[PDB]
């Protein structure tokens, strides 16, 4: 008689369980942490507030934390990212979860609340698991006293890490944090190879468009932009790349991409005259990957080739000026998370109008909105890092430290390279890869232990 | 012409070398941009730079840039097979002391470094060092330690040379401060990776003219050089397998689409023939070592390799392959310069029609420089623009003239600031015709950077 | 008004299907160009076409193009899993008889074909046939031979159907002429290859959401479908091995950078379990059959496959995989529609946490159409423009109206002329924005072609 | 004291022999035929005039032919394609060969002449092996009385095949021929994969230019154009493709290339106004692959980006209007087969002029001119077909038949598919590939013999 959740359809739990069982065979690092740590129960008594995409992969993460002794109460960090059978399976296991695919903003900011409050009172939470920093923000500003019992926050993504480092610089961060993103088994796995898998996947599911031979413009060439560009280029697209970082632009050139700017001479003065109309008039598909604001602006959207696809794979929907398109253009729903944006006006539309754009997931995270996000074997690395980060902070009860000792521990640091390598070895084992052991002679030559770490912290891989 | 302070293979190659020098200048905008940017300031006036790095056309553009800013130099190559004789001829014909030629013996190599160190039998008044691998750096610390009292810094190019400096620094035996030129993003993630992608299959084609598509390759190491080497072979259609001791690099090889294997059963190298995965090695048509380690392609692996397999090394030193074992036990038949068939049938001669042989390239030396020309000019543009920036910073620092307390604080191993790394990258992108977008002021505050950059924290790995 | 001559899953999906048809029209310029050129002339006025091909959004544009040119049609799908229900709904809502839904039983599949053949309990007065796979063609010859007396021709879509036509032709059992639509270059070297490149990994991801990069795949066959399938997996970062019986196709797989292996030791399929390369198959994460042959992934191969490997088929018929053996001996657990875990522990029941299972996609049926949506519109544009041209040509020839003596001289299986193949390609290129260069008169005279084409002899293989 | 030859340096013979022994290990199909037919000696009494690039690969072909009883007198079919160590080894073997790298046009015709005449009188030749049709043309126009003794011609390449068909169409072909080019183990192997290997190889040896990130234009997308485009794209170049054939242009699009024309709207009206100056101003490398005439014309050369590389990989140099460049621009030789073309004027040049183009091999076949052509393991397929074709035509004895019997056999034909398959099988085994054998039921199911042929003659692979 468990009555403490809200999902789309609880009858999907059996289907979710079947896909969870499959996902466990695809996540050896996360499941290896189950077998290695099951005995000592390091999260015994941990009460975790969790806000991250309620997918099948997150379901395995949740059950791993619970299997090690923790209690959790969960919601998604995006309105379109939940897999309804995953949320159903989690609720059926007696775990508080408040998520469904296709939430509104009111239902979104309410689901996060249902995790925060238990019977109208603050849950005795002592850990925070976040993806994007939204949950972290709500606690700091609306319930600032709850954080005096919390031993730390483990943040998943680049946007959340940057926002935390704002507070570390400004002195408003109330607990230490783990930069889970900057583990190599995360940033160079999740952010790059994950988007390589799921970008073209989501574009195919949404539109079924042939990609080979067509022109694409990728905004950004960081970790997500590198994977996004590869996802399209391996499909045969002609991919152009935009960047504000010259180093990332250099890699794009060396990787075989033409580097262009949406603006003449790269200067964005806000006018239509700044737009390279000849370039934008050739683009069949534009993808924003920046984590920045307004990188696909209104003037770009006016200049795009007719029937071009527009989508965002960055964390927030403000990469594209969707607000401009709501106010001025008529939206025609093709199917859930697929809209035709008619540039002829907003007072209705001609069903056979040829001057439209196709927007995916209403500008939200396209891989999770129009598909299922990253596959299990990639998220295995990110969530194994997530569990170890929860272990590191909970075993080092910062909230129980005296005030004088707190200052040395207050930081937003990564995990030690040893843990990063241990996650990597389990991932390599999943592929059947065989890592070579250094001889004692070889380890001395290059100056490392046979047991690692094998690189200085300055190494970039 | 009256000037005899050099030794090259053939001075008459200068005109040919000069013609290729002019072409390479058009391919190196960042280096040429520094030449024009600082010429009116002569930032290297008074600098007397000892240089030890492959005497290619690309190095000549670096050298003539250094001279253009006011420096005097005396140069040698850091490998016996890597010198382009027409590049050395043009440098010597320009009045620049250079001692390098293709096909040096071991003794001539050691002799060439000293001819730069000594002028007219006595030590030259050097004050700067440019080194690639640390051989010249080590020779100064060991055999000419008094010269280091007047030298203001070392700019080290490659990973192996950097490793030696960090050891001396930890030992307290390093005498002058150094700049890690290797770990600039416009060097390590450009030279080491993309350079080997261009030049690895380039060197293999020149040495053997072998079809690479459809054949099996084993790449030991998946660092920057291992990544680029594996891509150089995979893009030609090779079936590439990767070996690694670093599980993080091994994870990247899997995700990049390679099967990760070990030459030893379960990865355990206990020194026995029984430890060799004879089934795996018996399938390999080509083996490339990229680690910067010793004996990663060992004697038992050579015995187990498929007949007529190609063996080469692209790490700095030739000890990655047990070539001493092959010189001792098997007969060498030269096909052509830097290409030898190594007959595994015995020591005393060979059947001219023998089928059981291996092909070793560049006698184990750097195969891209030994059998081809190394990295193209446009890639070395980033690495050598960092060299000029590194030389300027340390020369304008005057370490040898600082107080003792100041000496101790700056006897470090540093890189270049990220701002200069970005400025180098910006010029290379413009060389491709790329256009970098400028942030708006509202966007720059949103992501917490300057509109002018730097755009990433120092922790960023790219 | 009162239209009931159809059977679909859900008529309320019609508005959704109409929206996707309007999108697909913008993606199929060759087919829509044919619709606009010929609509006013009504070249298919009086044509009555029995159609049997995957009731997809793409087929819907084909259907409405034939109708726009004046034909009447009665349609069914040629596979039980390939129908898109919103496409079938939109066609039925347009007043076109269509009998197709996703998830038909074998009984319902036969019934749907019959409902096209029969109108109100008696044979429809059909005079044209459009087929994909030859099922409708076989039923007409075996069960309704009198209907063929009034039929002017068959236009066959795929390789398997063309093989069945040639067997009937040489046995003297083919009653009407046919056009081999498959062997247009804008069909074979477009649909069969690039179409499977797009949709193979698409279907695997939708069915399993498995990571593909770094895993091992075995592709049986290296024809057009096998070439496109191997690329679909290799571009995702899979380690792809290829099996073939044709040495020429095997040679291409090698030159394309794949290792060519056989499921059987030395390639000898002696029917015993001992002939299976257990070590090879114990490493395979994914096996794809692309042959159009029978039992190319047999029971002994399925017993030897690595645990949790995915098994799927993209050839036309499901007998490429011995699924009957798996039905007879192993327990099936449905994950979701067209995704089954097959537990090799026994027939009667299974452990929910059993680790020894295989994942079968689409029950061995066409995986791209079964677990995804088949080829994209812009690719199917080439194939279906050929279909319209073939229907027009055979209908205008009026074979059925000829005397018996004339029918014998006209009875053949033919391909479309190269000139039409080229005009289809030109519209496809314009759809991408490509600009074809025009020969000068001297250039055309130099290579011996007309300025307007055709540009290649009929022997050219492209 | 046999001196019936003409080479550059006979002392290079030992080097050529060392590389010939290696090359023989790379050519199992060619060596396999040499071992198979040695006993019968099918070419005993054959007297072959041979005209094809004197490479190491050609050396293995020549030595095979002589092993079966044939006598040959050899020449190269290009002035720049000879490997001097291969010609030296052949001459050192007592075989008449007249070839060296860097012949003049007058020397080229002299080398053909030296094979045709023996002691100032026509040789009693009865077989012809040709590459490009140069020897075939000289026989018909200058030595017709000798063709009455010739049994057949085996032609290597597309250009020579095209010339054969026009002679047959005009009734001027005097002897039958076998089109070796259109075997699948030659056309879809030599012409495509060979250029994939040797195009970027030649550009690297000629200029040592970085290719990644730069813009390329490939003229043509036939077999050679397909391999050339991949040769550049696999190096990281941004490749655009030009074609007159829309079907080949369709393949370029689907293969992931942007299809463009040097002329506005693809219309070549002969004026400078028709040149797409914007496109050609951004091209760093142009490669002609057509076998047509003047596909990189003077107006295109005027509009090319400064310092762009120009090279041809078709059979003849007239694909580029090199004659215009000789008349109007000053040529500065960088090194053999590498010339700078200064567009500042004809009379002299500034050594530091920036307005130049880099021409490789003076417009001749760039892979053979600046490198070594196709690798040994690729030429194994082409030359195995040549040996089979020589055996078949010599055993037919066309020159002995009466006129009415001649008329029935005077044609240009290809080798049977069964022999095409047997050559491919040996190539596959060279890679260690294992071909699966059909079961009798499978063979019956698809209607082929267990032995093959496995495809109908209409199949395009
Ligand atoms: N959808 C997913 O699966 C997923 C996964 C991880 C991260 N993300 C999100 O994606 C975003 C990017 O993450 P990342 O790890 O790649 O970050 P990153 O900092 O490594 O890369 C972002 C890049 O965008 C560039 N950029 C910024 N503004 C630009 C502009 N106006 N024009 C061009 N380039 C511009 C920056 O120079 C930078 O190189 C973040 O918001 C992150 O949270 C999404
Ligand atoms: N030839 C060239 O053009 C060129 C250019 C740059 C650098 N290099 C040289 O190449 C070497 C590698 O440089 P890098 O930048 O790639 O260094 P790196 O440290 O980034 O990579 C070396 C890798 O080798 C791996 N490794 C070490 N021992 C191993 C073993 N026994 N088996 C398998 N893997 C092993 C390490 O884990 C490491 O990841 C250095 O010596 C450098 O000087 C050559
Ligand atoms: N699903 C789709 O979208 C789609 C599209 C086109 C064709 N098809 C179907 O796919 C099949 C193949 O079509 P295709 O055009 O590629 O035909 P194809 O003749 O060009 O290719 C089949 C290949 O399989 C090889 N083969 C046969 N038996 C084999 C065996 N036992 N082991 C290994 N290889 C073997 C043959 O040598 C041949 O090369 C046909 O049934 C066709 O109808 C499907
Ligand atoms: N260098 C080598 O190694 C090598 C090898 C084989 C063949 N070849 C030669 O290369 C040439 C091409 O051979 P192939 O087998 O590729 O022939 P092909 O017939 O298959 O291809 C030639 C292509 O050029 C296109 N074309 C013609 N005129 C054009 C124009 N003005 N603009 C653009 N495209 C145009 C045609 O449409 C055709 O697709 C022949 O002369 C052949 O002898 C060279
Ligand atoms: N060609 C080259 N010249 C100089 N330094 C190099 N390092 C690698 N390749 C080089
Ligand atoms: N190596 C080679 N030998 C002869 N002809 C060729 N054509 C292309 N490459 C060749
Ligand atoms: K997923
Ligand atoms: K170079
Ligand atoms: K589709
Ligand atoms: K060669």
Image (cartoon, coloured by chain):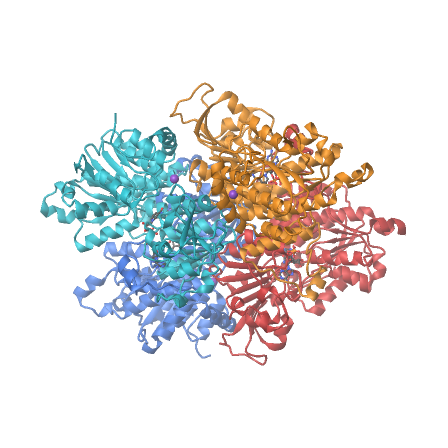
Chain colours: A cyan, B blue, C orange, D red
What is the quadrant of the N terminus of chain D in the image? bottom right
In the image, what residue occupies the spot 32% across and 43% down? A79
- Measured as percent of width and height from the top left, residue C82 is found at 53, 36
Establish if D28 lies above or below A119. Answer: below
Q: Is residue A77 above or below residue C140?
A: below
Viewer-nearest residue: B279 or C293? C293
Q: Quadrant of the C terminus of chain D?
A: top right
Residue D293 spot, x, y in % from top left: 67, 65
Residue farthest to the bottom, as pictured: D347
Task: Judge left or right: residue D234 versus residue A99.
Answer: right
Query: Residue C356: x, y in percent?
Result: 43, 26
Q: Return the residue nearer the eye: A265 or B52.
A: A265
State the image quarter where residue B384 is shown: bottom left
Residue C68, visible in the rendered structure:
yes
User: Could you tell me if residue B108 is visible in this image?
Assistant: no
Pick whichever, D151 or B10, lies toward us.
Answer: D151
In the displayed orientation, state which residue is furthest to the top. C348
x, y percentage for residue A449?
29, 44
In this rendering, is residue B192 above or below C137? Answer: below
Query: Residue C174 or B435: which is nearer the viewer?
Result: C174
Q: Along the horizontal axis of the image, is D25 left or right of C369?
A: right
Q: How many marks?
A: 0
Q: Answer left or right for B449 relative to D339.
A: left
Which quarter of the picture shows residue C98? top right
């Amino acid at each position: 008689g468990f009555t403490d959740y809200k999902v789309a359809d609880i009858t999907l739990a059996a289907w979710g369980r079947r896909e969870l069982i499959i996902a466990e065979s695809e996540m050896p690092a996360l499941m290896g942490l189950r077998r290695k740590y099951a005995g000592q129960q390091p999260l015994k008594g941990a009460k975790i507030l969790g806000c991250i995409h309620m997918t099948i992969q997150t379901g395995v993460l949740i059950e791993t934390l619970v299997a090690l002794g923790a209690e959790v109460r969960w919601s998604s960090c995006n309105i379109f990212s939940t897999q309804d059978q995953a949320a159903a399976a989690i609720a059926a296991a007696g775990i508080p979860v408040f998520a469904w695919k296709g939430e509104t903003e009111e239902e979104y900011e309410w689901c996060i609340e249902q995790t925060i409050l238990k019977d109208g009172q603050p849950w005795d939470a002592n850990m925070v698991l976040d993806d994007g920093g939204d949950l972290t923000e709500i606690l700091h500003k609306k319930y600032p006293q709850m954080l005096e019992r919390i031993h730390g926050i483990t943040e998943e993504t680049t946007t959340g890490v940057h926002r935390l480092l704002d507070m570390l610089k400004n002195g408003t961060l109330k607990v230490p944090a783990i930069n889970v993103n900057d583990s190599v088994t995360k940033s160079k796995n999740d952010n790059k190879y994950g988007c390589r898998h799921s970008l073209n996947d989501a574009i195919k599911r949404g539109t079924d468009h042939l990609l080979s031979g067509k022109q694409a413009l990728v905004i950004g060439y960081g970790d997500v932009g590198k994977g996004s560009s590869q996802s399209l280029r391996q499909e045969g697209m002609i991919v152009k790349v935009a960047e504000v970082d010259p180093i990332c632009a250099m890699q794009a050139c060396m990787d075989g991409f033409e580097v262009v700017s949406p603006y003449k001479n790269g200067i964005n003065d806000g006018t239509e005259a700044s737009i390279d109309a000849a370039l934008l008039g050739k683009i069949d598909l534009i993808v924003t990957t920046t984590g920045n604001v307004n990188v696909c602006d209104a003037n770009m959207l006016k200049a795009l080739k007719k029937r071009a696809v527009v989508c965002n794979i960055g964390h927030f929907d403000n990469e594209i000026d969707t607000a401009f398109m709501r106010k001025n253009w008529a939206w025609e729903e093709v199917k859930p998370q697929v809209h035709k944006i008619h540039r002829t006006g907003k007072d209705g539309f001609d069903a056979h109008n040829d001057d439209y754009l196709i927007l995916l997931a209403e500008g939200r995270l396209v891989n999770l909105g129009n598909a299922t996000g990253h596959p299990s074997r990639i998220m295995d690395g990110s969530f194994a890092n997530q569990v170890l980060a929860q272990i590191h902070l909970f075993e080092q009860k910062y909230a129980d430290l005296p005030a004088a000792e707190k200052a040395k521990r207050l930081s937003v640091e990564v995990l030690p390279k040893k843990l990063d390598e241990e996650v990597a070895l389990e991932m390599v084992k999943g592929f059947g890869g065989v890592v070579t052991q250094l001889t004692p002679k070889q380890a001395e030559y290059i100056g490392v232990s046979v047991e690692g770490p094998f690189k200085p912290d300055t190494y970039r891989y």
